[PDB]
Amino acid sequence: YGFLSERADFAQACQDAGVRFIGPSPEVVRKMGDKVEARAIAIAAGVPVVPGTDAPITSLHEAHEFSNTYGFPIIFKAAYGGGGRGMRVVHSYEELEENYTRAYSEALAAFGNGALFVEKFIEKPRHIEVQILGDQYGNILHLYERDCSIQRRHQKVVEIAPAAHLDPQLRTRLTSDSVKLAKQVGYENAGTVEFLVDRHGKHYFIEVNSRLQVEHTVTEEITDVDLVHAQIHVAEGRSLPDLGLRQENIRINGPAQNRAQKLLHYLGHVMVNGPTTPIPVKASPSPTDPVVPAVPIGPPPAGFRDILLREGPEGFARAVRNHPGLLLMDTTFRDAHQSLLATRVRTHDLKKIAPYVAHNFSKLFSMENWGGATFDVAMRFLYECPWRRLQELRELIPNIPFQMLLRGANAVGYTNYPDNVVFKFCEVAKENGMDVFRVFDSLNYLPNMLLGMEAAGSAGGVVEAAISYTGDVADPSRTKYSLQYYMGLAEELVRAGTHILCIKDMAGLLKPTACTMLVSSLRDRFPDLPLHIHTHDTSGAGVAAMLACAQAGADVVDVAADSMSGMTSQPSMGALVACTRGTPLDTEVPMERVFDYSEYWEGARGLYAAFDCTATMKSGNSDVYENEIPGGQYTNLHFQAHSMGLGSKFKEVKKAYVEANQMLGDLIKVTPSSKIVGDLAQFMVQNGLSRAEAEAQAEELSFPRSVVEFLQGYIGVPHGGFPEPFRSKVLKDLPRVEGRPGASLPPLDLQALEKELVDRHGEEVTPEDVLSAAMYPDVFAHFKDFTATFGPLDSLNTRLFLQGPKIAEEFEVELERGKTLHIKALAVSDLNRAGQRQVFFELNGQLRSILVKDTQAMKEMHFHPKALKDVKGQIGAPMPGKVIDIKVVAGAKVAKGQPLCVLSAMKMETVVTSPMEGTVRKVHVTKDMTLEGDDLILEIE
Amino acid sequence: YGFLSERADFAQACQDAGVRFIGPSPEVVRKMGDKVEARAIAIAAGVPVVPGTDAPITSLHEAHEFSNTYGFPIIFKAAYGGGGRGMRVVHSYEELEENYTRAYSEALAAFGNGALFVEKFIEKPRHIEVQILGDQYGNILHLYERDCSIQRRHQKVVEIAPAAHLDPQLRTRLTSDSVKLAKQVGYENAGTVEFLVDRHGKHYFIEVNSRLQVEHTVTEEITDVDLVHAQIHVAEGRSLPDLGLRQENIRINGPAQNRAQKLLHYLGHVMVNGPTTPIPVKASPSPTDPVVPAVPIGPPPAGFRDILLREGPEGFARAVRNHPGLLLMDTTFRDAHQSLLATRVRTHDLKKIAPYVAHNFSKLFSMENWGGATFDVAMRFLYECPWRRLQELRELIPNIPFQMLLRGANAVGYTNYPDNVVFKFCEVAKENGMDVFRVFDSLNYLPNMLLGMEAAGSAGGVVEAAISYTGDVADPSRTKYSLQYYMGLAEELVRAGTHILCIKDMAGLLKPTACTMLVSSLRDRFPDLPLHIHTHDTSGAGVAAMLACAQAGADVVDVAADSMSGMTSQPSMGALVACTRGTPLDTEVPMERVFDYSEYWEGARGLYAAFDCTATMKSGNSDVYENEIPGGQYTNLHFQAHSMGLGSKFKEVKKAYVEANQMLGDLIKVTPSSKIVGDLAQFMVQNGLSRAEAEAQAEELSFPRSVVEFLQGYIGVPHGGFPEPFRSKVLKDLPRVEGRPGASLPPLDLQALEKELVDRHGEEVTPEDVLSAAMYPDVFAHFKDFTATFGPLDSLNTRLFLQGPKIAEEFEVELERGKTLHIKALAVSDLNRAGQRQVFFELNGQLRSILVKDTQAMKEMHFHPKALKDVKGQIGAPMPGKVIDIKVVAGAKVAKGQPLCVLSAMKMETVVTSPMEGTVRKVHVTKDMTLEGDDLILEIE
Ligand SMILES: O=CCCCC[C@@H]1SC[C@@H]2NC(=O)N[C@@H]21
Ligand SMILES: O=CCCCC[C@@H]1SC[C@@H]2NC(=O)N[C@@H]21
């Protein structure tokens, strides 16, 4: 083969040497090997041809005239070319010049002749070809047409004989026209007249293969005619009739999943580029995986979930109130790590210990495992589905109620949503096995809590209304958040139909005396209502606070596994179990089971050393009674301060946090209000501002977006109202939200969103995907693109996820039950000319290689811009950030306070505003430019 | 396969996992995989079985009772064993106990269970087996019996279907009994009931293979039933009738060359272990290949070889004498590099310039390209065939006579050979295209020269008798090698029928006055004889010496290409051509052609920088008139002195060379006599001996083997005889050779040697291989083993041969005309657990990997031994070397001068002898031990 039948000079050289060529005559090989001559012969034989130029085109102008006459699409083809090279389809006039030039250069390089011709492009043709056989006596026998339509880039891959579902009349036309064409040239060998068949059943001649084709074999199998025997005997001078070959005697006789490669691509990416998750501290994960304790064979014992499923939320609440002793709940699944390892704990590690929890802790009130930061963090930083985590944990723990932290009018998100999104989220959360909804508001703003309670109750969930605790009820000088404030809010939440009343001490402010006073007052007022107390051990007094709550008549307290307790986490489970043992408050939890649970979590916490709060805080700190910083905010505020170069000033940041809380009006501090106070505190320290200076200059200063959105009312109304005149000075003419922010939002069309997601990602979009996109559109889009590239990263152990494999390291990855990948990392190559490294693996005893991309290998940048602090017209970047939008151009008049650009840094759009009226002289920045602090954005005159 | 159908626990584990096992049920696999259970079922089905025990035998007594009942021969078989292991035939009672014990131990070791059973041994059975197929509906279709009787140690080798010449009634019994057996167990897959058929046509069941056998293919080819399709469809639950399978429808129908991998293995070896050729200096080969000058298209012009081929040796000699002008000859092909790069120039580089030489230097008298050191060095260090070099150069240069340096009674070797080897060497050299034989002796010993002249003349070669020049014929104080000595030897060589007379000045001692005197005296005596003068430019006077010879009536002078001339090489070709231009001695060689030739060789010499004499000698040196060290010996003696730690004492070595020459009797100094003087000079300097001390202590000292063999007479007799009493003192009672050393050697049987080589290396042994083995047995053996491992290394360029490729380096290797390898080196791995590195290549766009061996990666040793110089009984190693042989043991009495051990260092067996009479107290060395200088060999008391 090798397209040698195109050439005749070899056939002639055989004849001149006195050696027979077993094929057509040199004249027939020449006539049929020239596509222009062969086409002219086909027209003369009355065989239909594709509409096309009669000669090779010499100019782009002839291609333009052809395109005007026949319309697009058209195809350029090399006049002297075979095998699919030097061919270009053109769909439009804009493409014509580029594709002509490329087709010409490719034809010149491949065939030594750049001559092109133009044809009409037949869209979605069948490639049908007819086997012919001729003798030296002018007998021509055709053979049944084959189907060669299964092609990759115009190369044949699979060939079928006869053509499947071909119209018998079309078959007769194809075979008759092949025999006519062959007779017209005096053809004398096995050969193949090729056609394109359009969707309307018209056939068009394209080319004749004068060489026994690769696919002759399927014709032999359906005709019982040995083509190579026939070729030899014809070259001996035998006639087709003498071979028994007559036309009347010839009859017809009879998305791939790539999960393993995507995982190897992730592992190769981490080996070349480092961790894909941002690492805050230079600590390495443990090299040893945690030891999983032994679990009994069988279903776990019946728990409080069996009561909830049998008797509903009110039956569950009565069973909790009637329980003899103290009930505990496990927050290790979410709250404990959110505080200690910043919610980085992966579904992989949670699943390993889940069967042990189900068997040995079946008497837990609930396990807190989802809501708070876990929803965003799972998608954004762990690249895993939070819903799959819920479903898989629910299968492994069938007997313990699952609890989530729900914001009342915001669900698990950072902004307000239309009510129908919050309702649909609670419905789908309950369907996926969520049982208890701890409904809180960041300001205790009752209208937001009532919506979340109604949404959770309408879903059929246990409504736990949570009052966020701030201040000190035992301090008579703190009048704003008095005992009467808490009692009055509890009365409104009980009237709203809460099944359980929670006190949420998010910072660890509840002193044992305040515990006794608050919990006894609530118990005396509500004798039949279950009381749930949540605290943090930030002060090192959380165990004593929870014992005081239990003695004052709390039915439930929040605890964590001992190795996941203390500091900014919950009180120790083992400490509470040991201290209540043999009292009327005994939890009946065996201490040995708490130890085995803690040992697993000690090993697992070692995998997260890169995120551990102990890198920055070695113990609990009693300054929390002054600063009131929540556990998860303390860790985040420290990492942010270090990233901004304020790490040495963190004591000033804590002092500014107290001042910022007062300036803002001493509001409750929990996500997102704790972040708003944090951003203001960092802003004050960064700019060297005292409270009095920041309040005096409030009309001139560009406050953090979170502070502005709070003052606008986007998170609800704080107790006692907003601080005036401070709010009016910061907002100026900015729009204000009155009442509940979600109440003015139009309902989101979830069916329109589902359709958009199906169009973008394919038919596997679920209701969980729609709700994830509705709450977190950019995060969900990034998560889908990332998992489309790298596959199911939840299958990797946490060390391999964070650091990848070492060279010569061998490990196992379970994709599904009974599908293990044995993977060994072998080598990483040097950088190629495309800026890629080749990573080599063994996968199930076989060499694999993946091309990866090393940005670190080739990284450089330059920052021009500086703003003179003394020149009011020079606008510097107020933070390191990326330019999202530029609102002004050079020569534009700008008013004082007018938006100039939008920076996106630390996951917060900051609008940079004009400090003066003037004319923009020059803009120094571009869209997507990265700026450092004080980089010159623009000049104003 | 692997006898896995014996096991059912896998079939059960598939069923328990919900995965279909494509085979019989786990119960059928168990029943049929147990030979005792399967046999009991065969008896119950009425199928004949071999007479045998009903249970596994527990005692030798049960084997005795069985043997009494059934008679011998019997066979022990493992009860739980397959594949012919744990089986023993017993022919007699004397064999019963041994064979039982062996069969039991083999069964226990192979299968974990020693249980045996006894059967009657069927003598000379046919092994006939029947293919069965069953479905889940109880349909069983048998297929025709196969013949598996062609066995080696009970393993099947050749299988036939149907069984050849099988009785049709026996076939029907076999197939009926297989179908009965299969029905009795409810069999459900393709399977094989096996039988032994005796010489009387009785069949006996042995075993059923429940796994699609290796030999199923011959059954498919005779039945047109795809067994694997049938196995799959039966496992889908289809019936045999629904598959069209009914018994009535089933009928009977009737060394690879690895050159590219071996080259990649060499390149990988050099990348891991470094150069395979010993590198004397820390210089790197040039990264640039030499530019080959343009060659005319066509055959080269007629030269002096066309005269030689037309008119024979005497016609050639007359044409040389009658030539108007000075003829030149090119030593560059051999002598020039032997002196400068120590003969490391490869066939690869010689071939590249050969066509240019043929066209532009067609008037050369000859080109010297083979003999001297080139024969051994090509095989030993370049791993290339010297004969292939001769043949390929002869094809490329058809028109210039080829010249070799031939030792008269030793050919190109280092020892004397039987005469028939020297004659056969000259014959095969002439057949391979050698034209001129420069016959010399290292001592001008006429009887050795006459044999070499007769051998070369009898082959039909041009005999050039060469007188080796030493001394100064212009110095009347040097009486030993006077003008009369040279004239008298010339008369004897002319009387012996030399065609050409050569003066070989191997050191560059011929001063212009001595040239004039010697050459004019020879010309006056022999007016019609061609005179050829060879010198070296070691003194920097060689050009002036050759001009004086040409003026005195020399017809030919030796020259080298300018970049390969001077120093220890020949005089410059360009200098001689330029100095004779426009005189009666004009060479008619165009200077531009000499420049292009020199430029190629300048580039090529850069590839050999690692061997260049300029590492040690920056110019010619006139001290050669005092030391008389030949060019090639100077370079070698310096490298040896540096390897022995005497490099800083090389001036003392040159002085000791003069003293050693005198002590030995002032013999001519050329290979091997120049080495003998060199070894003595190094020995004197190493031991701090003056001439007078070495002559006084000659009975006590252990001289170098080369000096001893010289004094014995193994190289011939020196002019003036051996030095007495020095010879008698060194030799003592050692055997003396009188006369010509080859004359007492029995003829070598070359046909016996050819047969030995064919038995060792296969049928590709040539007459050239036989002669190479006859002259250099150990070198030739090593060369064949090396080229068997690494392939045709002559195809590699010289840089890649010496240093291998760099990582990411791409290069071409031409194996044959039109067969190019594109090779890229990609990576080298770390050391594996087997002490190997994996080297990765791209070969013709494809990844290749080779496992190589890094001795350097894992190299360590320890030397205990030291000999106190003051303790006469402590025998130290006289040189660094390897222990070849140990001649004595502890407790042996030894006489003074008795051989103690043989050391092999610097390619020279040195016998270590006792300095005293005594008893060997202790031997400290082992065979193959490597010793340093002064390492304690043994103690004598
Ligand atoms: O880096 C960006 C923020 C990542 C999430 C931080 C969570 S949101 C829930 C909790 N409350 C806070 O103020 N921060 C953490
Ligand atoms: O390394 C061992 C010796 C290698 C060959 C040396 C050659 S033999 C021809 C010539 N004459 C000498 O004395 N040495 C060189």
Image: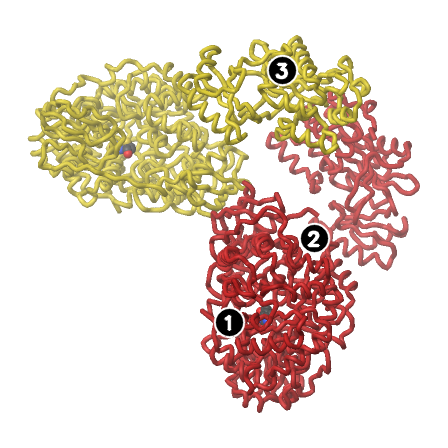
Chain colours: A yellow, B red
Regarding mark 1 in the picture, which secondary structure is present there? Answer: helix
Q: The disc labelled 1 sits on which kind of residue? A: Ala
Asked if one can make out residue A365 in the rendered structure from this viewpoint, the answer is no
Q: Residues within 10 Å of mark 1 (few under 14, many from 20)?
A: some
Quadrant of residue B765 within the rendered picture: bottom right
Measure the C-alpha gap from mark 1 to mark 3.
82 Å
Mark 1 and mark 2 residues within 8 Å of each other at the beta carbon: no
Q: Residues within 10 Å of mark 3 (few under 14, many from 20)?
A: some
Q: Is mark 1 within 8 Å of ligand 2?
A: no
The quadrant where ligand 2 appears is bottom right
**In the structure shown, which secondary structural element does the residue marked by tag 3 occupy?**
helix
Q: Residues within 10 Å of mark 2 (few under 14, many from 20)?
A: few
Mark 2 — residue? Answer: B109
- Please state the horizontal and vertical placement of residue A683, each as a whole percent of the image: 16, 35
Looking at the rendered structure, the kind of residue marked 2 is: Ala
Query: At x 47% / y 14%, what residue is drawn?
Result: A66
| Amino acid identity at mark 3 | Ile
Q: Position of residue A885 (x, y in %)?
A: 24, 26
Would residue B490 be found to the left or right of residue A322 on screen? Answer: right
Q: Nearer the viewer, mark 1 or mark 2?
A: 1
The CA distance from mark 3 to mark 2 is 79 Å
At which x and y percent is residue A595? 39, 44
Pinpoint the chain carrying mark 3.
A
* Numbered mark located on residue A650 in the image: none
Q: Between disc 1 and disc 2, whose residue precedes?
A: 2
The residue labelled by disc 3 is A41
- Residue wearing tag 1: B544
Q: Label 1 to label 2, Cα distance in Å?
A: 85 Å
Identify the chain of the residue marked 2, using the numbered disc in the image: B
Q: Quadrant of the N terminus of chain B?
A: top right
Residue in front for this viewpoint, B183 or B273: B273
